[PDB]
Length: 216
Length: 216
Ligand SMILES: N[C@@H]1[C@@H](O)[C@H](OP(=O)(O)O)[C@@H](CO[C@]2(C(=O)O)C[C@@H](O[C@]3(C(=O)O)C[C@@H](O)[C@@H](O)[C@@H]([C@H](O)CO[C@]4(C(=O)O)C[C@@H](O)[C@@H](O)[C@@H]([C@H](O)CO)O4)O3)[C@@H](O)[C@@H]([C@H](O)CO)O2)O[C@H]1O
Image (cartoon, rainbow over all chains, first blue to last red; front, side, top):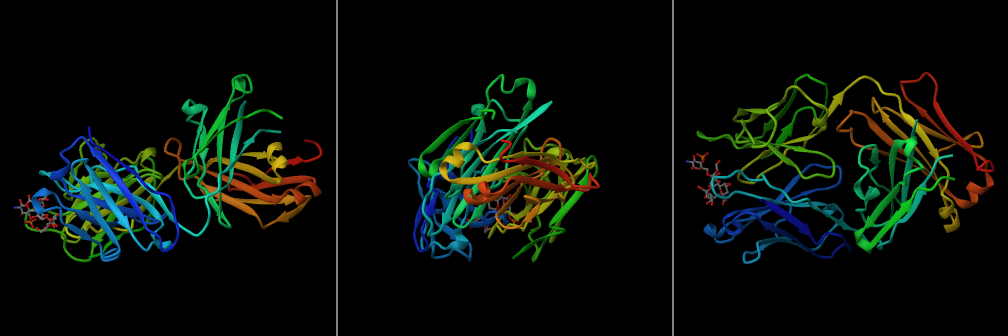
């Protein structure tokens, strides 16, 4: 049924511009307002604006904070809504969401996209170095994911087969570079007997690395 | 028009009533309707609609969540709180300028849990790359109050320590922490014993984890 899928996010230099899209399916796109909402990391949600339905002529409304700087537009034949952002600054660094707003008798913001992270900085794009963390009843292994930019990375273990006993920690910034670690606890009766591998992805640099956790 | 949320942060034990206030700076009601929405947001997920038009439960959402109020004063009620309820909750004006309130973080209270500490020396591939990080994980503890001191050859090291907490765990209500001691290979190789000491209320003395580099 209803799906909103975003893309276009990533790194952009201060003063720069960017266009995020939001592809919809599973409803009659033209009869619905669409909204854009942003969330700086750690902070509250902020409504940015909407574009109206066919009934109201596809007209647009923006929050006081982004009027004249951001533009919402739509491709009705493809069911995409866009958000064009110009003159980006530090404070614009956030996760950006699209959401179905009003349409038919329906409540707005029932459906949301997964969001896309926009980062505004002078800093370059650096791939992560991915290191295995091996030890010295249950056993804790890890992966250190060091020296990357910008966020996000994603980490899975055994391509998704291991999910409980996992703690992926939020990244920390150290002088232009991010460092993140993931951790997995498994029963020692299965290690190293059955293998354990962390899968790290950095889309911002086409990196996809697997690290087998090998004993010392 | 601004929406103000009550405590901003709230702790409630399992099984009990959580009550989150939302106050609007101006009435958001008409004769017919009160235009208030309530959302739930977990880390790295989009917000989820819980309550529309002030008191109606969204389809799919469990019946422990309920809303109420009119005019300017509104309430979200969660009873009984479950472990999966650990999250941030936002109210929102669901028409006109669609303002979001600032959020209330809900913490699930539970019995104390001692941390499980694991220490990890630099990976030998990282040493091959010319870096060195000593990582130790402090897993599945409660309350969230914890600190890590590092000792290199007996003396405390304050600089270059990266700390990171998970958000409260959806299943067991604990917190996890990653403490990464960042170091030049130079200083790694010139010293021998590495120690991370966790201070937590579950113990009258630090939970200590150690290794010697020459013994590796
Ligand atoms: N008889 C009901 C009347 O009581 C309701 O309002 P009151 O609480 O008494 O003030 C009214 C509410 O209708 C809206 C609303 O919020 O105003 C809008 C509804 O959508 C339509 C509609 O009437 O069906 C159709 C949409 O395509 C639009 O044309 C809107 C409206 O004309 C314009 O809507 C906006 C806008 O800027 O485009 C966005 C709205 O969210 C709202 O901000 C309105 C302003 O109120 C100005 O009108 O502007 O009208 C529905 O969205 C409706 C909702 O389903 C209520 O739960 O809310 O509905 C009467 O039936």
